[PDB]
Length: 461
Length: 157
Ligand SMILES: [Ca+2]
Ligand SMILES: [Cl-]
Ligand SMILES: [Cl-]
Ligand code: NA
Ligand code: NA
Image 1 (tube, rainbow over the protein chains, first blue to last red):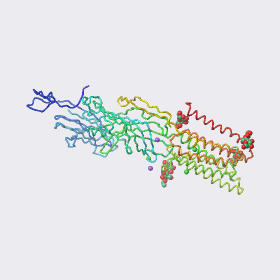
Image 2 (cartoon, rainbow over the protein chains, first blue to last red):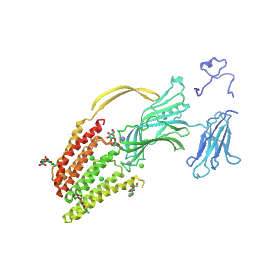
Image 3 (cartoon, rainbow over the protein chains, first blue to last red):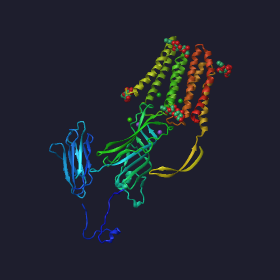
């Protein structure tokens, strides 16, 4: 291909030093710049929401002697906005003149210095935003009229969800980060190295920008807690201006999108947000690279499992009207449920049934002997399981079922006492009516409780 | 403990066709098993049989007092050992045996209640047939469970 960049030209007439690399200017002048001009014109439909109501676009680079025209127009019946042109420093070079009919605010300028580096402004500063949807066609021209954000393709993949802190509403994950992006200003000329590839290893895009003193697409994991353990870190740059970043990492992230209210029947969102650290006007995320399986299927492992992974490009505001790209890889998860209903629920059931079948007995002495004894087994079992249950400072559904379960088992002891007295007073057919009396209201209440909670916690009621 | 160590040279792909050497030293390991079957399995057994020999009794009153009491000892023991057992968020085979073990011990309490009422209704030779009735299906079920798991978890079935 053709190649690009800047050069130093030494021209010599009867001067053998010039072919030796040796340019010191001397003598009488013989040469210079050799010859409407070339024109460049651009469309863009700009949009002005409540969010974004001033907008500026840096122009790219006019020669002394170049003329610049720009025109705005309303898409619907939206108001005629304020137009102006300005240098990079903000000193004004023109203003918009609203036209003969009053439909287009046009502006004009031709160029003074050997660099004119112009900036176009359009504002909807004039009125209160009524529904925040007035949008404009903007025409622009000199005689790629606007200098555009270079386009980065980002990719992410997770290998291990290695920690979840349920109390502090955060988690930890191991994964792989790739950004690939074509910027000519990066360009390596080959004869220096003697290679196609230049490598920077073990440092942060930020640090390499600082070393090179140029702009690069730096980023941060948005909710990062403390430090990240990054290995196989690297950034590759070819001659072309094609560049790539590769980083396996192990990061700890705050996710207060946790809700543990329906534990263990809760489901959760692990979101891995990757924001840039430079605005939309310099770099933006343009593609998603499916460089590997996004979520890595080791299934035996099992503690939290994965429903679906959706990873997506979105632009978010930051300070100084920093609007910048954000690459959200967000895993959907649920707990391993066999662990809960087998280890917790099944046994619990049995403890509750023991209290219900001792109502059959009619030897209230013994009914109460077992009733009381089984309450201890309940409490006993309730702290067997207290380990896999986490302390948060608020009630999960399980904690809710468990209180009710205990309360019903304690009242069987209370009822059993009641009936034993009745037995020894010789109203034993009262106490036998009671026996069969409970036998049916009582497991009816467990079942109704459950229905209550399912509706209370699961059904948008 | 270590079963064998095999260490080996192999080349794997990386960034921009980086194909590079990898030196894998890979140890094979197993747990110290005496610790498990002595500390966990042997005692558990004993708790299991206590429930089976109280089926012999035919004083269902007392059968049930021991039956119930021994369930607590089971739960008690099950959390003695809860320390050396690690919380993962999913069932290991031990966790599997332990649930089944507890469930069978809870139904002895349930059966013991059943038989006691039968006794006081004066169908005591029903309840005595039951006694000998379990005595044999019940430790048959532990043994079949075990066979089930060995096949479920160990034998590529
Ligand atoms: Ca929250
Ligand atoms: Cl409790
Ligand atoms: Cl248990
Ligand atoms: Na984990
Ligand atoms: Na907290």
